[PDB]
Length: 97
Image 1: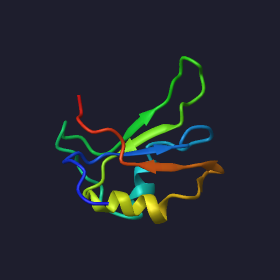
Image 2: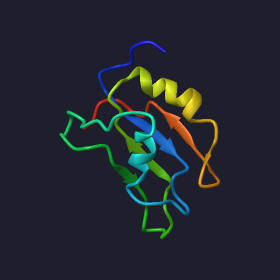
Image 3: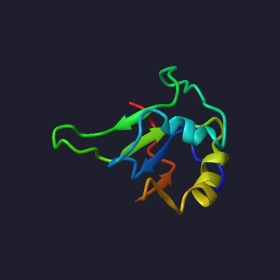
């Protein structure tokens, strides 16, 4: 585990085909508090879906309040499926540009 940067982001996979709306943030609220990220000052919603192919990419990132809670969510809160499609949680990429 340990300390990995001052960047709070988690990367989530498999949130695409048959997915529900911005409600995914409430899914993560079932284990935690919704954090306002200091990088832009917005609440945690990032929905990545390419409409250029017409079907969703399946990618989303959300910002948690504690960094150790992100690692713990990879252990118990991941390892299953969301809506029948395989989900994966990561620490994402650091340095918001």
